[PDB]
Amino acid sequence: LLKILLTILIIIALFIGIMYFLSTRDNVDELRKIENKSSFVSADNMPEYVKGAFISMEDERFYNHHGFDLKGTTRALFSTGGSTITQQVVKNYFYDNDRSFTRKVKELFVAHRVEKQYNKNEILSFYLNNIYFGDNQYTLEGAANHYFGTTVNKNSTTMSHITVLQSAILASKVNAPSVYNINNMSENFTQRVSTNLEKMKQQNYINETQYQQAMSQLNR
């Protein structure tokens, strides 16, 4: 008996070793291809409320972990469905197409590589720069200009910068239901972006004067 559960260990292992060999490759720095994007901006060149508008909702402890976050993985494993900003990256670039257990696992193997190789600001720039804001917008810059006419490059001087409110909108589309329309937001959506403005105030990405600003704006 103690050997039957063993013979199930080495198969999961064999399957995990199977899993590894299949992640290769799937090789970064293919990930660096992103940077050529016409409207590519880098996170260091954005406001900190824009950075946090995503961090706080999606990956509340980004610069901490090294790819995997178990307290959000357990919540996904229903001790309460979160992906690290690193895993989303991986998936979005490579696995944008398919989901399967045999993918989510190797997606852990790949995300590991990208933490090994890149740094947190690089990473988070692939994330913010290859994601869908539901209008055929896959860059935060594209989406920002496209929905509000504002920019996310803090060094910008030609276009008007992006407001606090707007950040929580775009952060909160990223993983909203395909139904959640930024052009016309639902009571259900306009409460989702709020769950967000709270997570930034809470996490200190914004102050109470900025916070009320958005929520008055949201209720405008």
Image (spheres, grey):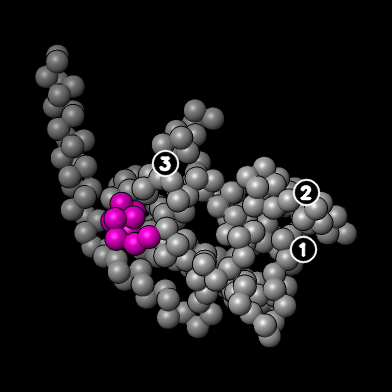
Residue 32, compared with residue 187, is above or below; it is below
Q: Residue at x 63, y 45 (%)?
A: 203
Q: In this view, does 123 lie to the left or right of 133?
A: left
Q: Which badge, 2 or 3, is on the more N-terminal residue?
A: 3
Residue nearer the viewer, 117 or 181:
117
Image quarter in which the C terminus is found: bottom right
* Residue 148 visible in the shown view: yes
Tag on residue 208? 2
**C-alpha gap between disc 2 and disc 1:** 26 Å
SS category of the residue bearing label 2: helix
Residue nearer the viewer, 92 or 56:
56
SS category of the residue bearing label 1: loop
Tag on residue 184? 1
Q: Is residue 213 within the magenta segment?
A: no
**C-alpha gap between disc 3 and disc 1:** 34 Å
Tag on residue 96? none
Q: Which residue is drawn at 41% across and 53% down?
A: 87
Name the residue carrying label 3.
69
Q: Where residue 208 appears, x then y in whole percent?
A: 77, 48
Q: Which badge, 3 or 1, is on the more N-terminal residue?
A: 3
State which region is magenta.
111-119
Q: In this view, does 157 lie to the left or right of 1?
A: right
